Image (cartoon, rainbow over all chains, first blue to last red; front, side, top):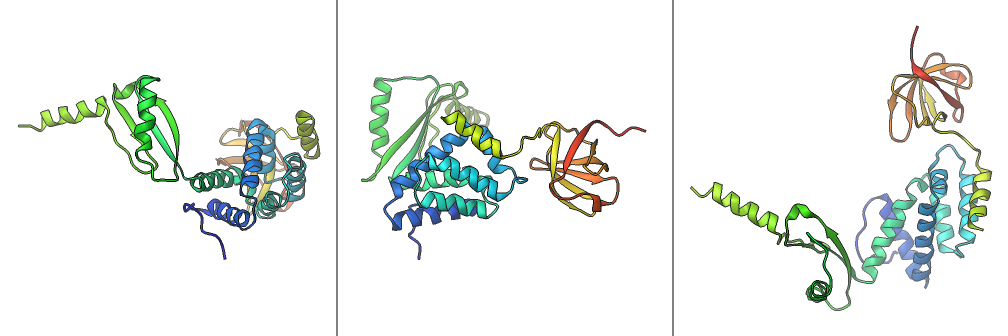
Length: 189
Length: 90
């Protein structure tokens, strides 16, 4: 018996992430195992020598679990994350330690109900733009939801607004709108 | 504290120059797959630990496929492969 994940994550890396999520939610360590995994991933990014050492297939797994154990005692990881990384180094699966962490981040984002929003504008703006954009994006929210907003700048769309949601997308931008109008001109008669 | 922890972790693993050297992952039927040789060229000669020569024919993202200039019974997994640095000449 495994607890159903909030969203389906695919691949072998998603299988490990759902196994870790199910084990952490059967116990009461969902927030703890997320905190040390994020701190572990931040440690691996801040020290690329550790990432090259774990992904090295020449080194024996005893040296990998010792290096994992030495760098996880400082994280104060207790039982789940230590066994999770011991399982990753028992198999030849710690080459994608970034993959399982990213998949586990995706599960926990949907656990809190956060929906990723991507809004693209030609020029950055705030005050009047950001206030109404937050309310407009909040109108798509069902109860029990959070907004993860990512703002992008791109002059190739002339102007307008290219706003995307977790699965939905619109192209209300000037560049695409004049493009289909000119296409209508060429296909008029 | 943090940097001392990094030195403690990396001190256990042996120090290797993976840009110019490499370690054999799998050897069989005259084909050696080696991890490392980051700056190796295609068609470039290599030297094994047993003195056998080889040529890098596949430069894959994970490993380098090397054709062995001899009997592969002298090559084991974990052997050091170095870069000659030049294409084959006679």
